[PDB]
Image 1 (cartoon, rainbow, N blue to C red):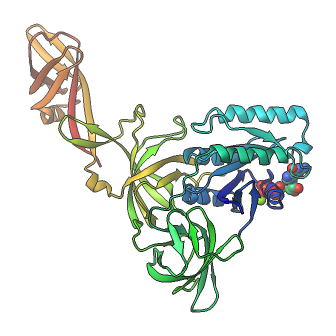
Image 2: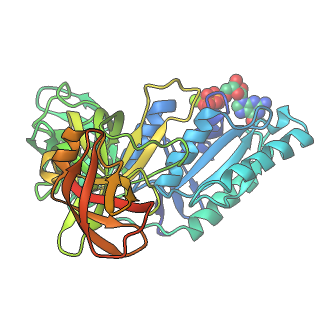
Image 3: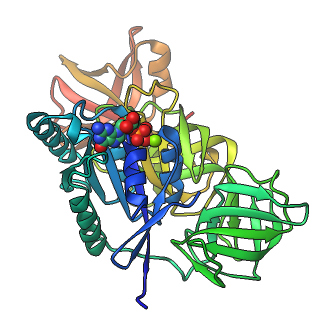
Length: 448
Ligand SMILES: Nc1nc2c(ncn2[C@@H]2O[C@H](COP(=O)(O)OP(=O)(O)O)[C@@H](O)[C@H]2O)c(=O)[nH]1
Ligand SMILES: [Mg+2]
């Protein structure tokens, strides 16, 4: 017959907004799927709030399209917001579906519609995404929703990665007996054939593939993007839990403690740069408490330094050094999601996102502090003094023999002397120094 294309469709939104009902309506035309044209569409499914999060963080590669449901009457709520954010960070095309249109008047629907438009405009990659009102109970606009899903899937670039090592997470695990186990999950990268030797991580065992179940059918081979059941031998299902990963033996996957990421910030005004910060880091399918130290990479003309962030977010660099409390499975280039989930569900919980550049500890990053002390130039008759670099004779004495520049005048000087008990100094300059001049003291420090 005709060649099918395998699609994974996520469904997101606040609870009671009609996620489940929409899913059921879609599935009638574990594993729950439906067909549109030649698209085989498997629903990415988790019960709710944090589960969808854990689902996207891990499965982002293979999630082609997402439906974000919003009640017509009460409009966007918090969870709608965080789902929107997450989907924006991971660059997943979305359709905004306004549910329960039968329970709302035209005016209300148009209102919510416009609110959603305004919201969509505040996002990077979701900037304009089509919005349809529907009623899953009534069937209102559902046909149009299907046609739209088709159009969107037609436009979006769907890249399945076969070429790399086989990489799949494990959602569920069923023992049969001591000699066998069945796991279920969607393949991220690579290819599997029946009778292959793979491994479970972090526990690092070695198992063989007995059976591949795809689309309620047995197949010899599965590919990335396919959501499959798999029977494997050499493991009991008690050892396999929420964070386990089945992968080939050529794998680049590592069990990691320290993670260095390149971080993009979601909302600038809600974001804060105070270093050594306690957050919840989403990596793969887990969420591990973590400590973060924001820093930027500066080229001084000879050596590249990693300097603690100057609190300026101008320029997009926010390399974060993360130290994790627990372990995690990661690869270089994996999308990582910084959340604060300690906060109540009532407020937006996303503290960032970013690509893992290196697995490295802070101590080896040679972290440094940019050090600037500013003081003025007071000149009485015949004598030049610098004020404000030191608050006492002790500190003033500590400063002797440093490098100092004068602002905007392009003039260099060294500070030799220490004047008075109040911390005044004396310095050697190139000539043409004037009263009330600006002195910048510049040096590199050991941070923390
Ligand atoms: N009138 C109407 N009610 C709906 C529609 N979709 C869902 N509901 C109702 O909303 C309630 C909860 O929706 P649900 O499917 O559980 O959404 P979820 O909890 O976010 O997955 C149920 O009692 C449904 O009857 C709709 O299109 N029209
Ligand atoms: Mg539900």
